[PDB]
Amino acid sequence: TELSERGEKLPAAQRRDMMWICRDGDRAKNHLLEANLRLVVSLAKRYTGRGMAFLDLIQEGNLGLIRAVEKFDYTKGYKFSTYATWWI
DNA sequence: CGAACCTGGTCTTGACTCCATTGCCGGATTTGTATTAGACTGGCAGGGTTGCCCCGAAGCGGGCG
Image (cartoon, rainbow, N blue to C red; front, side, top):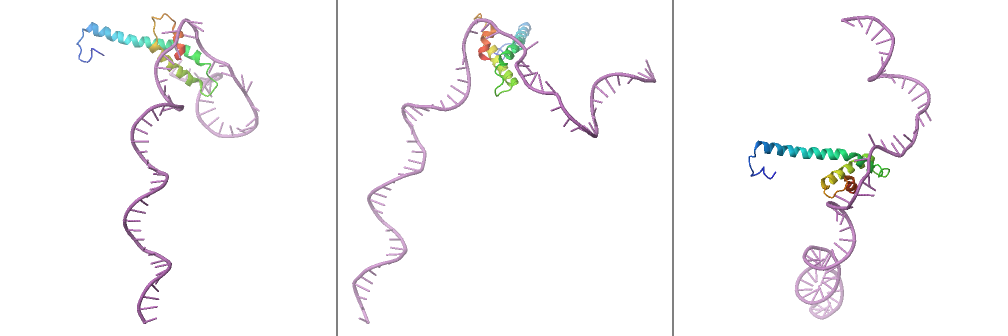
């Protein structure tokens, strides 16, 4: 995005693997969200029975899981559920 | 016989009062958003009941290419 405007006609290999990494990041993000959907379901099974329906609670948990996978850090050496339970 | 008078109003001038009406201003309360790092990973859940009728769809016996 920086080198698109006012930038450079990059080499073909550099632009091609730049697009490869740009696709791989979104593939990994979709893979991580689809991995932890089950954790969202297992947490949201207990807030039912009052007011809201079950599937709306599942969807709001999914949105919180989106925020948790956006703000998750790996260098703190903790597991992902430890951080994601707060946001969910 | 005229004449004051006395009193309906008709109206104005000037001072006074008084309360809306914004306008800041300082603070109070109200409302919205962001962030919490050990690990946690696929629901509880509640019932099955009539009678009659119409009609549309699934499936099976039965011949056929």
